[PDB]
Amino acid sequence: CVKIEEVEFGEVCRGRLKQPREVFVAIKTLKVGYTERQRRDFLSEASIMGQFDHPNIIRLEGVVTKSRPVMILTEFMENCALDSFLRLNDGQFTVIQLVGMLRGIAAGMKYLSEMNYVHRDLAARNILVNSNLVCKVSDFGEDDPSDPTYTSSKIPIRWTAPEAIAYRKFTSASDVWSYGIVMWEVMSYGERPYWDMSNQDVINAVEQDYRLPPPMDCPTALHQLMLDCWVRDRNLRPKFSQIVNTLDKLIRNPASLKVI
């Protein structure tokens, strides 16, 4: 039922699906000479992905394991990752549209969290965008390599709550910390969280109560909600339902988004 047009575990192609109407899709193929371990992990990521169903979580259309090569089919998102999408479009969206993007992402995270799923790598680079500007939470798919995005231990320092760095305490509340960072990315149109602070400086800074400032022209309401997400006391951070609720409050009362 699949076809491949313009082309970790293998390739990353653009394809076309035809189910009993035809759509564009994203296809992960698995390279020649994959290991049992490269095959076991590649697919179980599909398993993880295919237990979800929500308009802000990336859809697994399907998977074909009955032939070589074996594929994971997911939904096509024309505008790619949110962070590059925001960079290419600096200043081009209204505050309401940005809140809209955040609202969708907060809604996907509320779904995952009610499913007892902890994402662990929530970041703009893992949020995909379609042609209607709908943002969907994604996974399984570099400004300065000296301060890399990921540190091996698997941990994206700049996006990770201090208790998840220090003690591997990964929970929905650690995802909420990450969402705060995602808010800051969106509102700044894709700046690097913490800029030319070394990865180590960021851990040090955070433990010292440094929090990222408001992006240019960011409404005080929105920055306040970031600060809430970055409470050192994980128990005080809002839940994702509360974040969705706060963002809806702001959409119902847009005058309140004018304070800067």
Image (cartoon, helix red, strand yellow):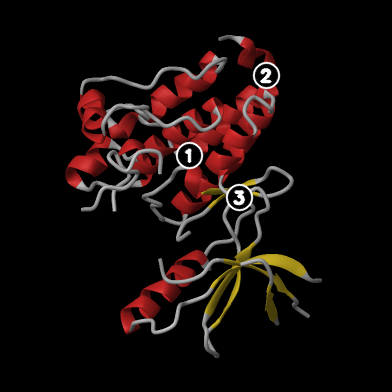
Which numbered disc, 2 or 3, marks the residue that appears first in the sequence? 3
Viewed as shown, does residue 1 lie left or right of 123? right
Task: Please name the residue that numbered disc 3 is placed on.
Answer: 80
Q: Earlier in the sequence, mark 1 or mark 2?
A: 1
Whole-number angstrom distance, CA of label 2 to CA of label 3: 31 Å
Viewer-side residue, 149 vs 214? 149
Q: Quadrant of residue 146?
A: top left
Asked if residue 191 is positioned above or below residue 111 in the image, the reply reads above
Residue 61 placement, left or right of 188? right
Q: Amino acid at mark 2?
A: Asn
Estimate the x, y position of residue 10 in percent, counting from the top left.
46, 71
Three-letter code, disc 1: Phe
Residue 115 percent coordinates (x, y): 46, 56
* Spatial separation of the CA atoms under disc 1 and disc 2: 20 Å
Residue at 40 percent across and 23 percent down: it is 227
Q: Residue at x 36, y 50 (%)?
A: 120
Identify the mark at residue 253; answer none if there is no mark: 2
Asked whether, in this view, residue 239 is left or right of residue 64, the answer is left
> Where residue 84 appears, x then y in whole percent?
56, 41
Left or right position of 252 against 216: right
